Length: 343
Ligand SMILES: N[C@@H](CCCC[NH3+])C(=O)O
Ligand SMILES: N[C@@H](CCCC[NH3+])C(=O)O
Ligand SMILES: [Fe+3]
Image 1 (cartoon, rainbow, N blue to C red):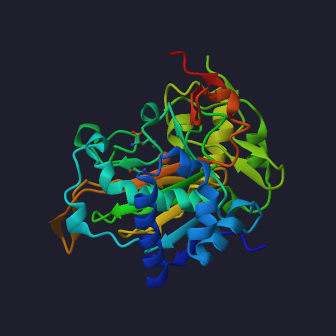
Image 2: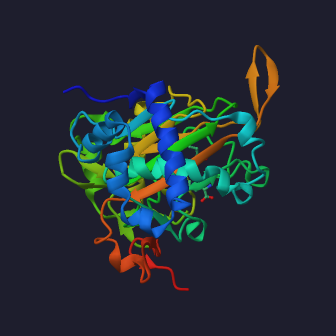
């Protein structure tokens, strides 16, 4: 067995970039925006017929691959060319993001999910939905917070929405700018190799999964030999109010001791790179940084602040139907491990 220790790196070609750009422009003209219900209803058809064939091939293989060799993450290097002057300055927070300008990017991202095949969704748990595409921008007000609006966060990893029974199946992180040169940290449950006694204890449904007395869940699930994972190191372990039992905390600490040595922080994304993640296999994180600066040869180089676009998707609308809005089967109303928001 070749135990995966790093994600698959795909170097996007100029011809592929040009196709994505032209297709993105055509979809903007045809449908106005990526949230158009006519576009969403025919998403897979546009994904398989408009994407560069190599991307379609990679994503289709990835969607059904839960084998021992699968890391659960793909880095698409140079997926898009970002014109930095046209993008202009990074807004102070995510509320300031111009969606007229990210519209083409939303089409491209939604086609990638569509080729898995997977359906872009939104969660009331994250920004009261906030649309299919989220701008992730470091806010000075929330500088050292354990969120996406954060800047100084270090050594931790998490799968997205570990507190939800219906968390995303697939995630995409499109980097518009990373002038601070912050590494993108990834962690795969497949990096452990063969099922061992430390991992086996995580199948027990005894762990707290606190929201971004509570119900418990298993950290490991799915296949017994090649499992899926729901994990949040900061929220389940290093949170004083996590409320874990001594048995559960001990199991998580033993797991974290093994897991932390397998974290991969080698990849530093460039503008236009997209990281595509199987949220059931691979956890993600970000190293500490001061937004709007980098240090080179003992000197501070001022720069525009970090800017990333996030899209989440589910492979089945049927199995999430008891937690979605009556008039919107793509809008998840789940609050915490089965419990729905009481509005
Ligand atoms: N910026 C995002 C990040 C949340 C997910 C990562 N903890 C938000 O405010 O919803
Ligand atoms: N969502 C992160 C950045 C993405 C890193 C994922 N490897 C943030 O706090 O901005
Ligand atoms: Fe996250």
